[PDB]
Amino acid sequence: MIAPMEKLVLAGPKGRAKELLQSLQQAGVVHLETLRPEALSAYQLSPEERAELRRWEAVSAGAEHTLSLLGLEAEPARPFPEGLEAAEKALSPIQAHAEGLTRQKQELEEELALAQAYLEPLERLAALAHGLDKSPFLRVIPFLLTEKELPLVEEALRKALEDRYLLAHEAYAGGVAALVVVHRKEVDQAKAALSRAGVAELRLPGALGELPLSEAARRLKERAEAAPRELSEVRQHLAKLARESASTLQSLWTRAQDEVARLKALEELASGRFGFALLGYVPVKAKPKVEEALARHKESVVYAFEPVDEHHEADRIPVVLDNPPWAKPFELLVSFLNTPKYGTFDPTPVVPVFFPFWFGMIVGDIGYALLFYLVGRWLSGYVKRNEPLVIDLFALKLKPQVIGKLVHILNWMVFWTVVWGVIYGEFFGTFLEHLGVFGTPEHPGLIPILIHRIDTAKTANLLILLSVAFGVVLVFFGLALRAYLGLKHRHMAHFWEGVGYLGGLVGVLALAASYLGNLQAGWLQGLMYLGFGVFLLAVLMSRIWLMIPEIFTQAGHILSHIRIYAVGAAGGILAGLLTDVGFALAERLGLLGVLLGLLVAGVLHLLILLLTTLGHMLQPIRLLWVEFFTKFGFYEENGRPYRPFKSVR
Amino acid sequence: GGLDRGLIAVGMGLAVGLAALGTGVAQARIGAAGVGAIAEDRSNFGTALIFLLLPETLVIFGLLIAFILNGRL
Amino acid sequence: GGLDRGLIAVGMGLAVGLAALGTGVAQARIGAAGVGAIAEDRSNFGTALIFLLLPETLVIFGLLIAFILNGRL
Amino acid sequence: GGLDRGLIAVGMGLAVGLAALGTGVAQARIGAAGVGAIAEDRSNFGTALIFLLLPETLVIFGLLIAFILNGRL
Amino acid sequence: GGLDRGLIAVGMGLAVGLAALGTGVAQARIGAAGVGAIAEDRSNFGTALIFLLLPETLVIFGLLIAFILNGRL
Amino acid sequence: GGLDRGLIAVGMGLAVGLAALGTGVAQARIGAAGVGAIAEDRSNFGTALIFLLLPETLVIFGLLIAFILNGRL
Amino acid sequence: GGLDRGLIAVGMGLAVGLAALGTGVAQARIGAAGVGAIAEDRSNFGTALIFLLLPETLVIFGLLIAFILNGRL
Amino acid sequence: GGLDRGLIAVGMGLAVGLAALGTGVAQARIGAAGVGAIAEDRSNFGTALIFLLLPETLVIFGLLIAFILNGRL
Amino acid sequence: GGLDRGLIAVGMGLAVGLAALGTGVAQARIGAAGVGAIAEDRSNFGTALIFLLLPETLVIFGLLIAFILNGRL
Amino acid sequence: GGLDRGLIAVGMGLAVGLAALGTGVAQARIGAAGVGAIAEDRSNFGTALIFLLLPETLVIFGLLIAFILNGRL
Amino acid sequence: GGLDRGLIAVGMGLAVGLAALGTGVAQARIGAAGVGAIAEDRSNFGTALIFLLLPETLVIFGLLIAFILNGRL
Amino acid sequence: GGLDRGLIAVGMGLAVGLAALGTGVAQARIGAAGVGAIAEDRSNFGTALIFLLLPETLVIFGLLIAFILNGRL
Amino acid sequence: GGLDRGLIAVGMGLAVGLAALGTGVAQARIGAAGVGAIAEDRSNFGTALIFLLLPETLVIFGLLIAFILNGRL
Amino acid sequence: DDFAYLNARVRVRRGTLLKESFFQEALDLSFADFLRLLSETVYGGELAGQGLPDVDRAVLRTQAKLVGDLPRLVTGEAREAVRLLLLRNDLHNLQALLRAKATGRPFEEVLLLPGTLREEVWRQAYEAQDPAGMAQVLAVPGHPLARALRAVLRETQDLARVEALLAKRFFEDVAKAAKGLDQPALRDYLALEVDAENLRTAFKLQGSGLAPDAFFLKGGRFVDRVRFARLMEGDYAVLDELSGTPFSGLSGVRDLKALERGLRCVLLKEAKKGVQDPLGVGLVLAYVKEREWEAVRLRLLARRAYFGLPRAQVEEEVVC
C-alpha cells in the first residue's frame, strides 16, 4: 500500500523556531511543505543566521576537500559535538598540512618527469659544447634534430664559418644534437633557415633552460639523484596525516552538513509579527515519534495533525510504500520506474508471487538452480562480512543492504527453479542418461516426468494454453483495477475504459475459442455477443474514440505471454543437445575420451549459461513492467517522492 | 499425403520470419531514441519502455498465424 | 489436395509477413519522432500515440486476407 | 486441377503484402514530419492527418486486386 | 488450362504490388518535403498536394496492367 | 494454351512492376528537391516540374515490353 | 513418392534465419547508442545492457517454430 | 507452343525491369543535385540536364537484350 | 534414396548464412561505436569488447539449427 | 534446344539486369559529387566525366557474358 | 534422379556466400572507424586491427558448415 | 537436350551479376570521395584513381568463374 | 551424370557472387575513409592500403568453395 | 558516422547545464557570491581563482572542453554535418591573424579562440612565406574555411583586400555546403542565419550610401536584394513588411541595439526547435546553441556583478 499521510500543522514564538527544528530533525520523519501561500510573511535569515550558514558551509567544503585530497571518502560519522569556532580551528591546521604536502608531491614529481626525459640528451649536448659553453660570439642556445633531419639542417648550417666545425652536426644516438655556433649572429640565421626546413631549439624548459649549458647538467643530475628520497618522505607523511586526521574530519563534515541543512530548512516557515508556523507531512505509522519529540517542549507548543485530502491536490501529497517483509525486497524491481500518485494502487505486492515463479518455469533445471544457489551463497559472503561489493569494469558499487535484497530475491527464485526442474526432469538438460532417476514411458526410471518438455510435438499445446491462461489472468486483473480506481476516484472515463476493454476481450477470447474448433457452441455465442455489446456500449458512453484501434494492443498483451514457454523450451532443448554431445564424445573416443567429452560439455554449458542468463532473467519482468503495469495507468501520472527532514547520521 | 506438409512449413516460417524482421526494424530506431532519452534523464523510463515494446505485437500476430497453420494439419 | 492446400499457407504467410514488415517500417520513424516529442514535452503523449497507431491498418488488412484464405482452406 | 486454386492464393497474398509494404514506406517519413509539425504547433493537425492518410490509397488498391482475384476463387 | 488460370494471377498480383511499392517510395519523400513547406507557410498547400499526387501514375499503370491481364480469365 | 501463357504473365507483371519501382525511386528524391526549391519562390515551378517528369520514361519502357508480351500472348 | 522432410527443413532453416536478421538489425542501433552513453558516463551501463537484450525475443520466436517443425521430421 | 517460350518472357521482363531500376536509382541522386544547382544559378541548367541523361544507357541495354530475346522467340 | 537428403542441406545452409548476416549487421555499428570510444580513452576497452561479443548469440543459434539438421541427415 | 532454351534466357536477363544495377548504383554517388564540383567551378568538368564513365565498364561485362551465352546458344 | 548432389552444392554456396556478406557488412564500418583512428594517431593500430579481424569469425562458421556438408557429398 | 546446360547458364549469369553489383557498390563511395579530393587539389588525383580502380578484382573473379562454367558446358 | 551438374554450377556461381558482394560492401566505406586520410596526409598510405585489401579474403574463401565444387563436377 | 552514437553522448551532456533559476538568482549577487555559484557548478572545474579574467578563462576552457570535441568524436558524413556549427572561432582566428600579419604586429599580439583546428596551424600560418602556402597549411579535406580562402585568393593573391572578401565568401559557402547534404534541420537554420546576417549588415551600413550588391549575400530564405537595398537606405517600413516569417517580431524596430536583441532571440528560438530530430543533427545543433547562449549570459552576469551596475541595464538582454 501507499502509506497514509497526515499533515503536521504547527505554530509558536519566533525565538524558539531554530531550536524546534533541531528537535524535529533529531527524530526526522516529516516532509516539510513551504508555507508561502498564506496571508503572513515568509521567514528570512538575519545577517547573524546568514553568517552561521556561511561559516558551516565553508567548513563542509573545506572538510570534503581535505578528505578527498587525503584519498578518504566523505561518508557520514558521529557528529563533532563541540562549537563552530572549535570546528573551524580543528579544520584549519590539517587542511594546511594536507595542501602543502600534496603541492610539494606534485611539484617534485612534475620536476622529475621533465628531468628524466633529458638526463643523457642534455649531458651529451653539454659534452659537445664542453669547452664552448660561454663562447664570446658563439654562445648560441642548444639545438637538436631527427636522424634524417640532421643532414637537411646541416645543408643550411654549413654557412656558420668556424675553425673547429660548422653548425652542421649529428653527435648523439638517441636524437641528433646541434648545440653549437660558429659565429652566433649568422648562426642564429642558419638555425632559423634550418627551422624553415624543419628544426627546433634543444633548450627545453625546466632545468634544461633555466640555467646555462654549464649548469643544466648539474641541475638535472642533482634533481634526478635526489627526487626519490624527498618523494618517499612526502608520501609517507601524507599517509601519516590521513590516519591521524580521518575520523575527526568526517565527524566535522557530518556536523557541518547537518547544521547547513537545518539553516537551509529554516527558511521554509511562515512568520508574522511575533509567531511562526510550519506545515509538513508525516506517514501515520511514524506519528508517535513526532509526538514525543514535540511533547518535550515545556509549553506543549501549539500543533495539530490534520487528515490529508485525496480528491483535490493529491499531486502535492508525499508518497512512500508500506510493504510486508516478504514483499519489501522486491520493491527494488519497481522503484526504478516512476513514483505512483497518492491514493493509487502500488503493484509491489504482485511481483513477489509471479516473477520468481515465471523465472523458475522459464529455466526449470536442477543443475542450473544449484549453480544459481552457489553464486547466491558467494554474494551472501559480502553481507556476512558487512563489506561493499565493487566491479570497476562496470562501475558497479553496491552496499551490503542491496546485497541482502538481491540474495533474498535469488533464494526465493531458486526454489521455483528447482520445482519446475523436477516437473520437466532436467539437470543440465539430459542427465537422466547417466542414471534413470527421471523416466519417460519409453525409459521408465524411478519417477515419471510430469511434462517432458523436449517432445515439442506432444507437449507444446499444453504449455501454450498454460501461458495464455497466465496472461489472461494478469491482463484481466489489471483492467479490473483500472475500472475500480476510475469508480473510486469518480472518474467515469477510466471506469468505461476498464469495463469496456474487459468486455471486448471476453468477446475476442470467446471468438477465438469458437473458431479454434471446440466440440460445442452452447453459451459461447451468447457470451461473445454480450462481450461485444458491452464493448460497444462503453465506447458509446465515454464518447471516446481511442478504444477502437487500441483493442488490438490489448489482444497483443494477452497473447505475448507465449514467451514464458518459448525462452524456456529453447533453453532446455539446447541444454539437452549439449548433454547428448557430451555422451557422444565419451562414447566415440571411448574411456580415454570421457575427460574430453566432460570438459567440452561443461565449457559449452557455462558459455551459453553466461551468454544467455541475463535474457532469461529479463523476459518475465517485462510482462509485469509493460503488459501488467500499463493497464491501470502506472506511468500515467507522477507522485511526489517522500523524503523527510532528517539527520545525515 | 504429399508436399502440402512441406509447403505449410515454408509458409509458417515465412510468416514468423517476416513478422520478426518488421518488429526488429521498428525496435531499432524506437529504442535508439529511448536510450538517448534515458541518457539525458531517467524520468523517461516509462515512456521509452512503453514505446520500445509497442511494435512487439507484430511478431506476436506472426506467431498466431504460424500456430493456426500448425493446427490446420 | 496436396499443392492446393499447400499453396494457401505460403499465400497467407506472404500476406501477413509483408504487411507486418510495412507497418514496422512505418512505426520505426513515426515512433522515433514520437519519443523525441515526448522527451521534449509531456503534453504530446496522446498525439504521439494516435500517430503511432495509424499504420496498424496495414497489419490488420494483412490478417484479414490471411483469415479469408484460412476460411477458403 | 487443384494447383489453380492454390496458386491464386499466392497471387493475392503477394499483391496485398507488397501494397501494404509500399504504403508503410510512404507513411513513415510523412508521419515523422507530421509528429514534428504537431509538436512545433497544434494548428497543423488537419494538414498532418490528410497527408498521413493520403498514401492509404495504395493498400486500398492492393485489397481491390486481392478481392477481384478472390471473386475468381 | 488450370496452370494458366493459377499462374496469371501471381503475375497480376506481382505487378500491382511492385507498382504500389514504387509510388509509395516516391510519396514518402514528397510528402515529407510538403509537410515542412506547410509548417513554414500555409499558402504552399496546393503546390505540396499537387507534387504528392503526381507519382500516382505508377500504381495506375500497375492496375491497368492487372486489369488487361484479368481480361485473360 | 497452358503453361507458357501462364508464365508469360509473370514476366509481364514483373517487368511493369520493376519499371514502376525504378521510376518511383527516381521521382522520390527529384520531387523532394523540387518541393524544397518551390518553398523558396514560385519561379522554380517550371524547372522543378520538368525535372520530376523526366524519369517517367522508365515506366513507359516497362509498358512497352508489357504490351509486346501481351500481343505475343 | 515425396520430398516433404526436405521441404519442412527449408521452412525451419528460413524461420530462424529471418528472426536472427531481425534481432541483429535491432541490436545494431540499440548498442551503438548504448556504447555512446557508457563512454560519456559509465553509470549508464545497466540501462544500456537492458535495452540491448530486449530485442533477443525475436530469435526465440523463430527458434520456437523451428523446434516445432523439427518435431514433425 | 512450349514451356521454354514462357521462360523467354520471364528472362526479357527481368532484364528490362532491373535495367530500369538501376537507371532510376542513378537518376534519383543526379536529378536532386541538378535541381539544387539550378536553384542556386540558372547558369547550371545545361550541365545538370546532360548529367541527368547519361545514366539512360542502362535501360537502353536492357531494351536491347529484351528485343533480342523477343526476336529469338 | 529420396531427395530429402539434398533439400535438408538448403535449409541447413540458409539458416547459418542468415544468422551470420544478422550478427554481422549488428557487429558493424557496435564495433564502429567501440573503436571511437577506444580512440577517446583506453579505459573503455572492456565495456566496448563485451558489447561487440554480445550479438554472437544469433550465429550460435544458426549453428544450433544447422547441427540439428546435420544430425537428422 | 529444349527447356534449356528457356533457362539461358533467364541466365541472360539476370546477368545483364544485375550488372546494369551495379553500374547505376556506382554512378549514383559519383554523378552527385560531379555536379557539386561543377557547381563550385567548371575547371574539373573533365575529371567529373572521367570518374562518371569509368563504372560504365560493369554493364559492358553484363552484355559481354549475355552475348557469349547467345553464341553458345 | 541424383538431384541430392546438386542441392547440397547449393547449400554449400548459399551458406558461405551469406556468411561472407555478413562479415563484409561488419568489416565495412569497422575498417572505416579504424582508418579514422589511425589517421588521428598511429599508436591506435593494434586496437583497430583486432576489431577489424574479430568479425571474420563469421565466415569461419560459414566455411565450417560448407566443409562438413562437402563430407556428405 | 537436358536441363543442366540451361542451369549452368543461370549459375554463370548469377555469378557475373552479383560480382558486378558488389564492385559497383564499392566504386560508388570510392569515386565520390575521389571527385571531392580532386575538387580540393589536383596532386591527389593519381592515388584517388588507383583507389577507384582497385575493386575491379571482384568482377575479374566473377567473370573467371563464369568462363570455367562456360568451358564445362 | 544428369541434372545435378547444372545444380552444382548454380551452387558455385552463387558462392562467389555473394562473397564478391560481401567484399565490395566491405571495401565501399574503407575506400572513402582511406581517400580522406590520404588527402589529409600522404604518410598513412601503408595503413590505408592494408585496411582496403584485408576484406579481399572473403572472395578468396568464396573462390575456395567454388573450386572445391568444381573438383566434384 | 552515427547519430545514434553521437546523440547518446550529447543527450548525457545536455542533461548537465545551468537552469533558468541559476541566472534568475545570479542577477542579484555580489561578485564574491556569484563566484560561489560559479565555483560549485560544472564551470568550477576550470575556475583558477578570483577576478574577471579568471571567470572568462574558466568559461572559455569549459566551453572548449564541453563542445569543441564534437567534430573529433565522429568521423565521415556526421563529421561534415556537425563541423558546420563550430566554424566562427576559426574565421575569427584567421581574420585576427591576417590583420596582425598585414599591420606587422608580432604573433604574441594575437589571442586565439579554441576552434576546429590545432594551434600549430595558426603559428605556421603566421610563419608562412605567402598566402598560398598559408592556405595549404590551413587546408584539411572538406573544411569550408580553407576553401573560402583559396577562392578569394584567385580574386586577389595578397593581404589587406582579403579582409573585405573573406567573410562574405565564407558565409555563403557555409550555407551552400548545408544545402549540399540531406539534413533538413541544419539547412533551414543556416538559411535563417544568412537572412539575419544580411539584415543586420544593411542596418549597420545604413547612412553610408554604398552599392547594395557588394554587401547582400546569397542563400537567404526570407530577405532579398530589394528589401536589403531599401533597408540600407533611409527606410524602416521594410521591417514592418515582415509577416509569417520568424523575423516578423522586428516590426516597429528603429535601433541597432533593439535589432541585435530581436535577431538573437529569434535565432535561439529557431535553434531550440531542432530537438524534434532525435536521430539527426537538430539535437546537436540545439545543444551547441543553448551552450553558447549559456556562456554569453554567464559572462554578462559576471560583468553586472563585478562592476556593480543597475539590474535594469541587464534585465532586457538576458530574458529569452
Image (tube, coloured by chain):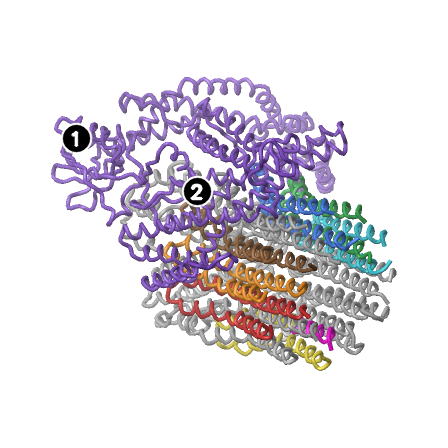
Chain colours: A purple, B brown, C orange, D red, F yellow, I blue, K green, M cyan
Q: Which sits in the foreground, A30 or N298?
A: A30
Regarding residue F52, the answer to whether it shows in the image is no
Q: Quadrant of residue A597?
A: top right
Q: Does N298 sit left or right of A425 as displayed?
A: left
Marks 2, 1: nearer the viewer: 1
Q: Which sits in the foreground, A126 or A563?
A: A563
Please report the bounds of the magenta region as a residue range.
F1-16
Residue D32: image location, x then y, percent? 48, 61
Q: Which labelled disc corresponds to residue A16? A: 1
Is residue A287 magenta-colored?
Answer: no
Is residue F6 magenta-colored?
Answer: yes
> Where A366 sits versus B19, above or below?
above
> Where A404 sits versus I56, above or below?
above
Regarding residue D45, the answer to whether it shows in the image is yes
> Where A432 sits versus C32, above or below?
above
Q: Quadrant of residue F49?
A: bottom right
Residue receiving disc 2: N57
Residue N219: image location, x then y, percent? 50, 67
Other-residue count near label 1 (Cα within 10 Å), few / some / many at <14 / 14–19 / ≥20: few
Q: Is mark 2 on a helix, strand or loop?
A: helix
Q: Does N54 sit left or right of I28 as displayed?
A: left
Q: Which labelled disc corresponds to residue K61? A: none
Q: Is mark 1 on a helix, strand or loop?
A: loop
Quarter of the image with the C terminus of chain N in it? bottom left
